[PDB]
Image (cartoon, rainbow, N blue to C red):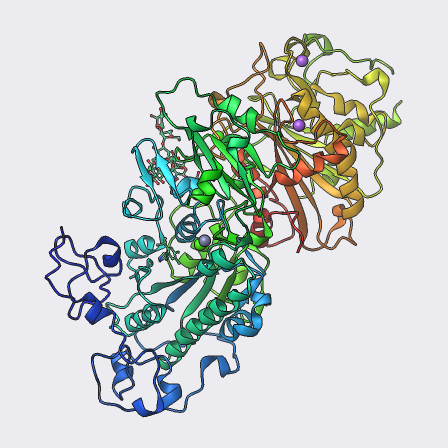
Amino acid sequence: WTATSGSCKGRCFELQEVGPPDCRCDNLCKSYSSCCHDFDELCLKTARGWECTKDRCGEVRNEENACHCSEDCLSRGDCCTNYQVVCKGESHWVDDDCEEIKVPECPAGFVRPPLIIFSVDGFRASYMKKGSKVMPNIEKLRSCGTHAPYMRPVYPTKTFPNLYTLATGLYPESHGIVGNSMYDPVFDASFHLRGREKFNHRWWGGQPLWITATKQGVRAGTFFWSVSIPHERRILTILQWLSLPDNERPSVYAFYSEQPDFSGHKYGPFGPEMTNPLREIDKTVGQLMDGLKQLRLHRCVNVIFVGDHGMEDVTCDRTEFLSNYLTNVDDITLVPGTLGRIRAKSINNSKYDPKTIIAALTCKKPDQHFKPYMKQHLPKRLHYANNRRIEDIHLLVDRRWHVARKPLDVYKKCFFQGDHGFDNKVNSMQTVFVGYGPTFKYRTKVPPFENIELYNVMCDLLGLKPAPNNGTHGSLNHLLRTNTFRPTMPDEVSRPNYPGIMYLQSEFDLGCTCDDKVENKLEELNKRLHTKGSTKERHLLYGRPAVLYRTSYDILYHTDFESGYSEIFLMPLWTSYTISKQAEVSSIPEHLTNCVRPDVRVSPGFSQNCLAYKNDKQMSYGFLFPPYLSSSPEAKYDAFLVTNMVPMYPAFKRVWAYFQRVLVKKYASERNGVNVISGPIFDYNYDGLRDTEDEIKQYVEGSSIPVPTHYYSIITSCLDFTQPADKCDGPLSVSSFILPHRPDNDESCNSSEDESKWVEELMKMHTARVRDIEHLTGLDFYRKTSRSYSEILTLKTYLHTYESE
Ligand SMILES: *[C@@H]1O[C@H](CO)[C@@H](O[C@@H]2O[C@H](CO)[C@@H](O[C@@H]3O[C@H](CO[C@H]4O[C@H](CO)[C@@H](O)[C@H](O[C@H]5O[C@H](CO)[C@@H](O)[C@H](O)[C@@H]5O[C@H]5O[C@H](CO)[C@@H](O)[C@H](O)[C@@H]5O)[C@@H]4O)[C@@H](O)[C@H](O[C@H]4O[C@H](CO)[C@@H](O)[C@H](O)[C@@H]4O[C@H]4O[C@H](CO)[C@@H](O)[C@H](O)[C@@H]4O)[C@@H]3O)[C@H](O)[C@H]2NC(C)=O)[C@H](O)[C@H]1NC(C)=O
Ligand SMILES: Cc1cc(OCc2cc[nH]n2)c(C(C)(C)C)cc1Cl
Ligand SMILES: [Ca+2]
Ligand SMILES: [Ca+2]
Ligand SMILES: [Cl-]
Ligand code: NA
Ligand code: NA
Ligand SMILES: [Zn+2]
């Protein structure tokens, strides 16, 4: 019940909210049917429109008008944004030359530059270049401020997941808004775009910027705008708030536009009808900037121009139908569209089997435009698994396509020409970032970054301490003129042991064999020095990784590679080696095919054993440093040490062997040497974080050898590729991956073919940031470089996407 007979007189767009049944004048009242009777009249005035005209100059105030042109309007803070231009011979902001904003130039009483987040729905990254002729205000912001060529959204590339990630710095799996439609089995409630349940507060986790601000003494304007409030009114309201007294004035504001997304759906990303929405957005920016200039705030306010996602060409005829694959189609609930999420129609149905669903949807048609996954097998870079609102079965849909349950769903709902929601690596899903103001840099381009990073920056712009989030604080320091955050490297928790030769061959009863007893004082001192770490500066280019949890491990040195060997997990946490441009691939010689050698530095009791692999009919083994890349026949023996062995399914060995035999050398040729760090990852509870030993769900049969869920590699070289990887003066270049350790290649539809036709494609799909690998291993890389720490942070958040420009 609303007692809508109270009043909005003087309370229009109240910042604080009144408890029902006192009626509301806040934005958001419209959505709840709770506005006071006089809301529209007092708060949504429209009389005479949005602009001053020559005749209105100096007029007598009329409180009915949408905005004002009377002499008193500036100190009332309610002039039309074009007031000075029309009535005082001022120029539009867009017509003024830009000038560096070296310091904030703010009116007395501002304690800090305000921040205005100007968010535009569906604003695809390429609109900045393609629409440049019709967006002169945005183009001035972009060229004069700090801009990236694009900003990476989170998956799924829908509206509320992205806007809420901007607000919190969290992956959707952690903030809880994991899609535009959701079922939460603990609440037993649903969340939809239409309607009221989405306004319930239990959907929304983490801590959004407006709460972070309020808790720390900074006042905030409201972020959500009801669809029936026109854009001009949203701007004028922000401008009114900026005129409040110092004790009441917010420091952070958001504007939101439903365009260009709304038109994008109807006409496609580049439909001729798209020019007009872009013009109108640009005009709104012009209104904000003219309004700020009138208030003398145009060299004081920091403005962020940001989209939530891009937009792709999608039509009704590009729909895959689950009814073409499944016979049981009525026993399932599909969340449909540009992604698929499948669960059982009914929890009473014990017949329903996810396994047979997956199999019925896997590689069934030659050009199949979606791929089914258990959520835990989705590429780790999507961070899309650790939430009860995400169904166990997921369909990743090809760009340009839709998935639906039955044809009747599509034509009983062709309407639309655009949609979004696909994989957040897809070029058409990329959106925009521009930062303009005293705290941002002047005329500076920065590389593309992920929207999860912005919360930290907005906290920095406001002098706030950010709530714990998924950004890497400091990785965006290069956007800022000042207010940078100067982070420190995390401290190592566990220091390594450096074992020497402590065990005799015969102490080992591991069931391992090697043809190797083939027997000089020159190269006897030689081999000892290698084992003591003589070549380490060649293979450990950026220092050893720090272990940031409590554990027991040993550093092991070798001619061709260095490793940090875990006595708890009985394998390396990491293995580091450099392959120069000149290096040679050799094969495993015949007399060494099944050779596994005891490591006399490491106790039999902290070693793997060959018998377990023989007994495990499902499990084979591979090597972290590849024998193929050994520097000499004698160094090759080191590669067969039991301490270099890891559990691998035969199907995964096809992948791994091609990466090590073919791809590493290819990358070294193309990149002028590479440094490689490889190792295992254990993420049995799919939370994106390193498992403790007691979380491991699978061991090599009859042993305590734990089975990794993934294998990673970090491949580093010189950004200036005229310098070899091991002699690099300046910035680094990196690409990484986190490959799922799977007993089959069902993910790769073309896997019956030669690895040269599918392996690299699989690796690209599972591209990763170094930071993703850090979360998953509890390791911290690049500790010893000649680069600044913020630069290394930026490097660790880099994602090689394998999309064209
Ligand atoms: C991205 O950044 C985020 C933010 O930093 C990282 O997420 C954090 O990770 C931590 C580790 O998983 C996690 O810490 C846990 O907190 C538990 C208390 O949680 C509540 O309080 C916090 C703080 O205010 C709050 O934010 C939480 O909100 C979550 O839950 C509600 C739903 O209930 C949601 O509305 C909200 O969106 C959010 O959900 C997300 O997180 C939870 C996990 O907490 C997931 O389940 C959801 O799917 C969703 O993703 C909570 O309200 C605390 O209870 C935990 O402590 C247990 O575990 C430790 C391990 O040290 C153990 O020692 C403790 O004793 C305790 O164990 C006991 O409970 C066990 C489990 O019930 C039980 O099995 C044992 O037997 C024990 O008795 C734990 O410390 C932190 O909450 C989240 N924060 C957020 C916001 O998600 C995230 O990891 C980053 N991602 C990556 C890839 O890096
Ligand atoms: C910039 C911005 C805008 C925004 O909402 C705008 C909006 C959407 C529909 N109507 N109004 C949100 C929430 C949606 C979280 C409230 C966050 C952020 Cl970070
Ligand atoms: Ca959107
Ligand atoms: Ca885990
Ligand atoms: Cl969705
Ligand atoms: Na085996
Ligand atoms: Na296959
Ligand atoms: Zn949309």
Residue 365 x/y as whole percent: 63, 32
| Residue displayed at 15% across by 53% down | 19
Question: Looking at the image, which is closer to me, 379 or 225?
Answer: 225
Question: Looking at the image, which is closer to me, 139 or 328?
Answer: 328
| Residue displayed at 54% across by 72% down | 139
Left or right of 122? Residue 610 is right
Left or right of 362? Residue 715 is right
On the question of residue 549 being in view, the answer is no
Q: Quadrant of residue 560?
A: top right
Q: Quadrant of residue 233?
A: bottom left
In the displayed structure, 166 sits above or below 185; it is below
| Residue displayed at 45% across by 32% down | 342
On the question of residue 413 being in view, the answer is yes
In the displayed structure, 784 sits above or below 526; it is below
Q: Quadrant of the C terminus?
A: bottom right
Residue 443 x/y as whole percent: 57, 71
**Ligand 5 sits in which quadrant?**
top left
Number of labelled discs?
A: 0
In the displayed structure, 639 sits above or below 54; it is above
Residue 562 x/y as whole percent: 70, 32
In the displayed structure, 640 sits above or below 784; it is above
Residue 741 x/y as whole percent: 61, 27
